[PDB]
Image 1 (cartoon, rainbow, N blue to C red):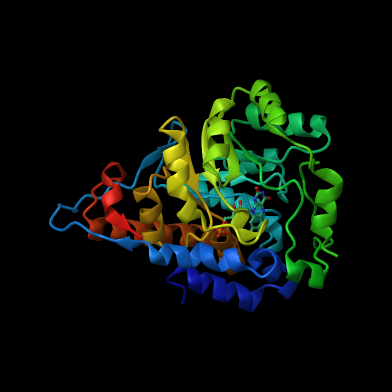
Image 2: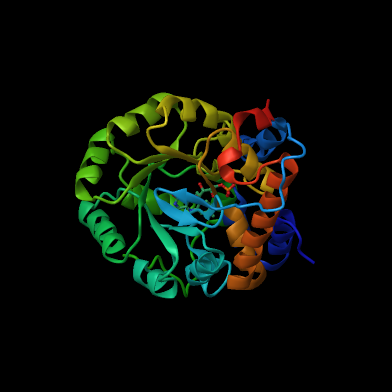
Length: 344
Ligand SMILES: Cc1cc2nc3c(=O)[nH]c(=O)nc-3n(C[C@H](O)[C@H](O)[C@H](O)COP(=O)(O)O)c2cc1C
């Protein structure tokens, strides 16, 4: 049956209700960036070295000082229990099995505590939105800290929700037996009521004083903004267009990655998400300077197939495709994945 990430998406389309599949699949508006996040990877070509000795390929690396088994981590995707009953709990258990990290959504269908208890040994980080209610915001950060989450990924590209046309057509909302457990399109209205469109760099200063955990700015697309995040004492940049779900017509993340890596001058780690489906995608992102990449939708499709096992399978497919891509390119470990491997 399912031997690559595209197969898991096709299976998911066959077994999820239309409104749930569409919520997970959609991009904003005409979905130009959604297509480009995938097409852009294909424009970057690989220049493999031969005869390097790849008997022993080591995929391990570090994210903000914490070891991971591979440079492929789970990105925040809201409300995972729509795809499968165990939702976030499963994801975290799969991450623990694989030895990689899970970024937990602020809009999870499982609590910060339920997920930590399910994956105590897993590397876990919290994705944060700055809520209008700063007491809501602080108690999410404090709960992450106490529960041995290792970083905060603050999403900075969502003052308002993007306009995902299928959610508006389907009048998206949660199934009746589910909730966000940490507290037109139903979700766009929720954002308008709950999430602060006023936040500025002053709020980043606030958050940077609030916690000693590492903080990564998620959703940066400009070098100037990245340099501002470094000036504010943040510890990494996640180059992201929110899975193409926010402003349509922004570039693909793999295309803006080199500007961001150049702008930060090695001062903080730079990560990528958006369109990662294949081991060669991971290799290209690392060659252009990313420390690791995050996967969003493939994880949801792993849930839709077979829950915890299905997330494990998706992660193992990515790991094996990445291993093969490294070996065929002449790379024994991630430290030798250099810029000459790629050209656009
Ligand atoms: C269904 C879905 C729900 C998402 N929920 C969140 C969220 O709660 N918080 C967040 O910061 N980003 C959210 N994102 C954006 C993802 O973190 C990530 O940037 C994006 O999925 C990466 O692209 P990919 O799906 O192509 O891998 C979501 C994306 C999707 C598809």
